[PDB]
């Protein structure tokens, strides 16, 4: 709930929901230290076909414990206020689940 | 009022509103036998021909006393400030009414 | 000034701006007690061949001094900070002026 | 900085953005006592249907020192944080430039 | 974190967002040397009337030690909560990479 990460993770949900409504692809930097894999960096794309992740975005995720996913389609955006499942989530066309971070 | 359910409950509104404006359905995990019922969990879907609701959303509504409703068109969005009717409500194409939980 | 009403009025405004840009009409629970009439509740419809306000929206309204006004086509949307028109105002295609409450 | 005027100036930035992403013309109440003329009130006009500010929007301005501007196109939205040019700005098709008040 | 540069930089986030979902182009007053290149002023432009920056926009950028960039088509929108890479970023069709100021 602290500056500056509240605004970043806020854009995340904006990117999240924008992906789901517009159909636009994303790239994620997603920690495998949790199931679902919490997302750490998300990159909404408009253009660049098979050529997904920007070089910039790649360079900041190999440095990282996280993995990296390109050209994902986000067809479901989820919110849950039960406690044992509290938190944002995004699902792919391929039925893969990610938690969105929170800060 | 408080963080973090100020996040997911504002996300519930942003999800509700998207669906009412866009036409895209939602799947809820909602109270069943009340007026209004209350959503404990929503998912905003687009394409999604491998599942009405994603299995991530199904399973998590099987860990709850509440019940899973899926494929629902919402066609109205109510913001209300009178005394004992203050809150957020959505209506479905077929008359169902929910409250959008606040916190 | 304060929660939760801040969340509602905010939504009132989103609904306001939403009806202007899309055509989608609204139903209002309106105070003739001021001029222009202050908006106490707004329903936002996508729906169909309208029938009209949702029964839930009418029941809350008729428990109040407010007059119901239904299926209005909002064409103008104002923000004004002149020291006597200090507030928000939607304008219906019929001339009608409605303040958007604040809290 | 403070309530409720933050809300209206906030709308302006949302009304401004709505105007440019949309080209629905606007109506302005602006004070030439500055340059760019600072935006004291704006009206987002949709099914204006041959253009024309609302009698209500007009009246509010004629009673103030500002000056009414009608039928105008917004094509550029500017955010700037340069030390001598901190502020928000909108530009028309006729090259005209207005400043958006801050709150 | 303070007033009034968060209002602005937030509106930089929205312009940046908007140009990415809509294909609109922006012109940018940013630092000259920088990798990534931090944004000091962004202008969202529907058109195209006159291609390129607005005269207003130009003159606030010549006065500063900053680069004017004109008609950049943004392609990626990176919300990053990275440890070495925290903040928000956009990417241009040319693989240019701009940090969006925070405040």
Image (cartoon, coloured by chain):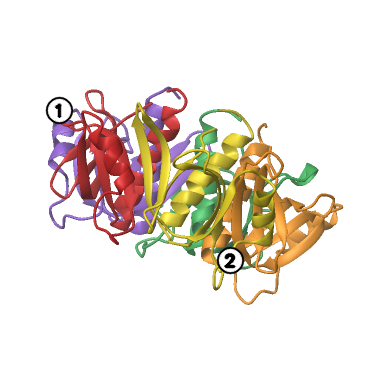
Chain colours: A purple, B green, C orange, D yellow, E red
Which quarter of the rendering shows the C terminus of chain B? top right
Mark 1 falls on what kind of element? loop
Give the chain letter at badge 1: A
Residue E47: image location, x then y, percent: 31, 59
Q: CA distance from mark 1 to mark 2?
A: 57 Å
Please indicate, yes or no, whether residue E87 appears anywhere in the rendered image: yes
Q: Which mark is residue E19?
A: none
Name the residue nearer the viewer: A54 or A38: A54
Picture coordinates of residue E62, whole percent (x, y): 23, 35
Image point 20% across, 43% down: which residue? E69
Q: Position of residue C86 (x, y in %)?
A: 67, 42
In the rendered view, would you say D86 is above or below C87?
Answer: above
Q: Which residue is found at the position 72% from the left and 62% from the top?
A: C96
Q: Is residue B51 above or below residue B43?
A: below
Q: Nearer the viewer, residue C24 or A80?
A: C24
For mark 2, give the secondary structure: loop
Residue under label 2, please give it: D52
Q: Residue at x 18, y 28 (%)?
A: A64
With A56 as the anchor, is D44 left or right in this view? right
Residue that badge 1 annotates? A63
| Residue A63 pos. (x, y %) | 14, 27
Label 2 crowd (10 A; few <14 / some 14-19 / many >=20): some
Disc 2 is attached to a residue of which chain?
A: D
How many labels sit on residues?
A: 2
Graded by Cα atoms within 10 Å as few (under 14), some (14 to 19) or many (20 or more), the crowding at tag 1 reads few
Whether residue D26 is situated above or below residue D36 in the rendered picture = below
């Amino acid at each position: 709930k602290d500056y500056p990460d509240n605004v970043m993770t806020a854009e995340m949900r904006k990117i999240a929901m924008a992906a789901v409504l517009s159909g636009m692809r994303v790239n994620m930097c997603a920690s495998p230290a949790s199931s679902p894999n919490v997302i750490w960096a998300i990159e909404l794309e408009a253009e660049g076909s098979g050529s997904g992740a920007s070089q910039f975005f790649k360079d900041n995720c190999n440095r990282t414990t996280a993995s990296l996913v390109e050209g994902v389609e986000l067809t479901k955006y989820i919110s849950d206020i039960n406690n044992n499942t509290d938190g944002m989530y995004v699902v792919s066309s391929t039925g893969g689940v990610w938690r969105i971070s929170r800060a």
